Image 1: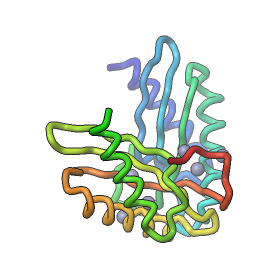
Image 2: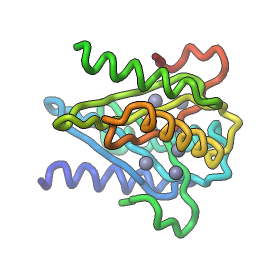
Image 3: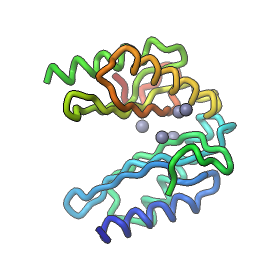
Image 4: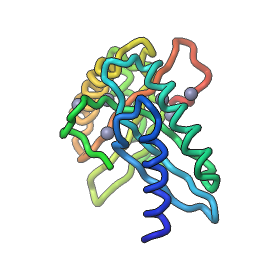
Length: 91
Length: 91
Ligand SMILES: [Zn+2]
Ligand SMILES: [Zn+2]
Ligand SMILES: [Zn+2]
Ligand SMILES: [Zn+2]
Ligand SMILES: [Zn+2]
Ligand SMILES: [Zn+2]
């Protein structure tokens, strides 16, 4: 599984590099031909408004799509995550 | 496709019956044996905090799981949706 491991590692690394991201909670990706399609959920400050959270999703989209050009489609959305959360999964 | 059509119709109807839901934006469901597994994204007020949005996700979970007992697992999260949004899909 190294091909998709390396892709998912790079997606997570790029998304955690965006300020406002509190970990990656869910991520699934797949190849379609040579291209990649992915769905991701990031953790964010629960006190952010949803509008504010979205601006983090858009930053993550930009960062990830920009660092990994084989990604043809990427959907990013958010869930709440408190600091020191052990209630949700993460990478 | 009537079996899954009827299930998805019932999921959407039950979720839109929850105050705070601004449409169902994304929904995918499948059978695993006789049981159903689903992933849904609801629209919410962009001005809600993420914490507040989550309380809507938990209400939708409760409503949907309660009305459709063949659903064994259901993940609900949110995205922003302004009133009169034509920028995101919906059911
Ligand atoms: Zn978003
Ligand atoms: Zn956007
Ligand atoms: Zn979406
Ligand atoms: Zn939620
Ligand atoms: Zn919850
Ligand atoms: Zn989740």
